Image 1 (spheres, chains in turn red, green):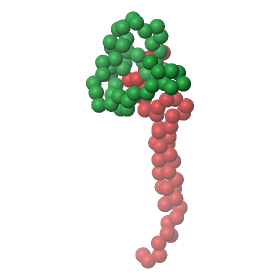
Image 2: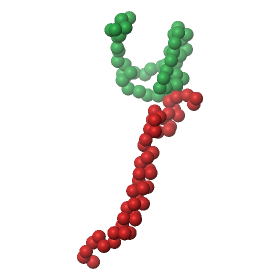
Image 3: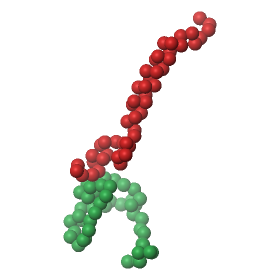
Image 4: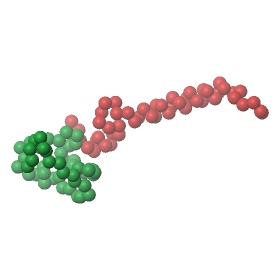
Length: 49
Length: 49
């Protein structure tokens, strides 16, 4: 009841899953060498070739 | 028209521009666009031209 942080294993498992998912969803904001990180913009800007 | 070493710069803002007349006119020897498709110009909105 009083002492906290006695459940480190379950807590850190949850933290690991959440962190992996967050970095996966954050990876969507990278140019990867292209001109923009959003697909609709480059679709609407230039020629399909 | 000014010299190449003293190229004349003009700023265009707060206007409604029709780029089609530029593509329609045949008076231009070279009409080369790099970041955008020439036919999509009327479909976009910019600032500080």
